[PDB]
Length: 49
Length: 49
Image 1: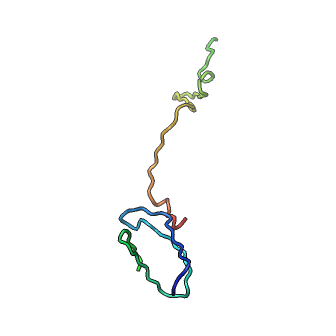
Image 2: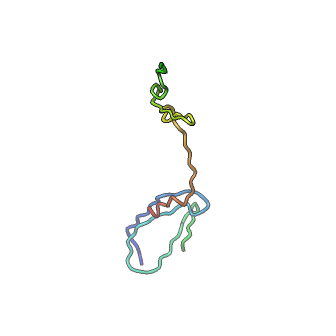
Image 3: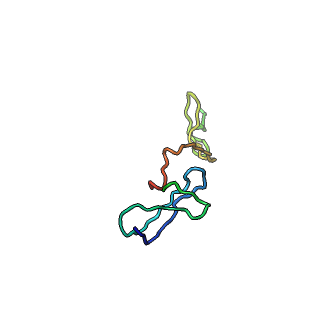
């Protein structure tokens, strides 16, 4: 499922050692299925495959 | 016969007196520093807000 309408934002980031940023993103896909997510620079890290 | 100015009736800043024991209440001057320590249980993340 390809996606459109990429609207990401960050309500509260805190540069801690735990998951100190919960980024909220609204989108619009094409259909139903799995979707992988990935960070392309090494400044940040994600906990969800 | 000449007690005159009672401190109940002549108190500056509108304080009142009360006896046994002596105590002056409501001396409206100055300002109170007050601190509070509180854990994260009563708060909640913006992901619930």
